[PDB]
Length: 104
Length: 104
Length: 89
Length: 87
Ligand SMILES: CCCCCCCCCCO[C@@H]1O[C@H](CO)[C@@H](O[C@H]2O[C@H](CO)[C@@H](O)[C@H](O)[C@H]2O)[C@H](O)[C@H]1O
Ligand SMILES: CCCCCCCCCCCC[N+](C)(C)[O-]
Ligand SMILES: CCCCCCCCCCCC[N+](C)(C)[O-]
Image (cartoon, rainbow over all chains, first blue to last red; front, side, top):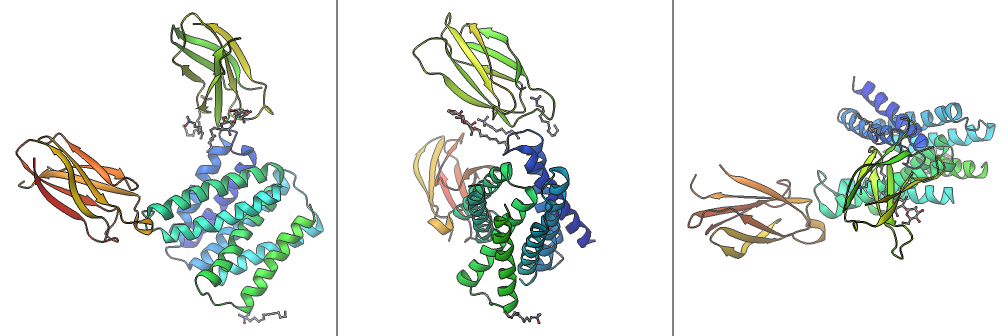
C-alpha cells in the first residue's frame, strides 16, 4: 500500500502544478490555495511512502508522475504545444530526472 | 527572462533541499531559515515563470535543475560516487533542458 | 471586473469601515491593497495590503472632517480596473 | 552544548530576567522553551524564538525559591539547563 500513497503523492504534484498555472503568480485566490495545500499533501504522503519505500525509487516515481502529469494536463487544459521535438526533449528530460533520482 | 527565472528557481530548489537535511527536525535556526526563504523564493520564481511558460515544461526544467544541482552538490560537497550511469543520466537531463529552450 | 461595489459600511470621525464585492470564486484574489489619502491634499496616500479572502477592511487614524479618497486594488489590473470612492469623515 | 550559561541578569521579588548563550551560527535552534516553578512541588512554561537569548519570567511569589529551566527543541543538542533562584 506504501506504493499507492506514493502514486497519490505524485498525483497531487500534478494538482498544485496545474493550480499554480491558474493562480497567475499566486494572485488568484483558490488556485493559489489549491497549490499550497497540494504540495503539503504531496510532501506529507511522500514522507509517508518514503518511510517504507527506497528514498531513491520513491522520489523517481514521485517527480516522474508529477513531471509527466504536468506535461499531459498542460497540453490538454492550457492547450500547450505538442511538437515532435518537444515531446522528445521532454522524454529525454524526464528520463534524466527519473534516472538521477533512481540511482541515488 | 522567464527561463532565467526558472534557472534561479531551480537553483533554490536544491538549496532548501540540502538545508532541510542540515536542519534537524526543522529545529536548527540558520538551516531552517534557509529552507523557508529558499522554498518561498523557489515557489515564487516558479509561479512567475509559469505565467508565461508552459506548466509541463516549466515544472520539468524546474525539477530537472533541482535534480541536476543535487547531484553536482553531492559529488562535490559530499564525495558522491560518480557513475557512468549518472553521467549519461545527467547528459540526458541537460540535453532535454537545452532542447526545450531551443524549441521555444 | 474585480473588486466591485466599494462602499463605506461604518464610519467614525477617525475611522472608516469599507467593503467591496470580491466577485465569484474564480474572481477571488490572494490580496487586495487599499489606498487612502486626503483628496487633493499635499500628503501622499497611505497603503496596506488586505488578505484576498476578505471583502472588508477598516481604515484608522483619520483626520475628522477631511475628505478621503479610498481605492481597492486587485493584484493585477488584468482582472479589473481599481475602484475608488470619496468619503468625508 | 546548547543551550548553556543560564543566568539571572536582573531580578525583583516578583520577576526574573534570565539569559543564556544560544551558541553560534550552526547551533542556533529555532526556539527555546523556558519553564519556571517552585523547587519544592504545577509548573508553568513559555517559549521564546531561537534568535533571542533572553527571557523574562513574571508573576512569581516573593521569597519562594524557583527552579528555572531552558530546553532546546530536541535532546539532540546537549542536555537542558536548570538553575535555582529565590526571589
Ligand atoms: C501565498 C499566496 C498569497 C500570498 C500573497 C502575498 C502578497 C504580498 C503582499 C504585498 O504584495 C505586494 O505589495 C506591494 C505594495 O506596494 C504591491 O506593489 C504595488 O505597490 C507599488 C507602490 O507601493 C505600486 O507602484 C505598484 O503598482 C504595485 O505593484 C504588490 O502588488 C505586491 O507585490
Ligand atoms: C559515451 C559512450 C558510452 C555510453 C554509455 C556509458 C555507460 C554504460 C555502462 C552502464 C552500466 C551500468 N549498468 C547498471 C547498466 O550495468
Ligand atoms: C474555508 C474552506 C477552506 C478553503 C478556503 C476557500 C475560501 C476562502 C476565501 C473565502 C472567500 C473570500 N471572500 C470573497 C469572502 O472575501
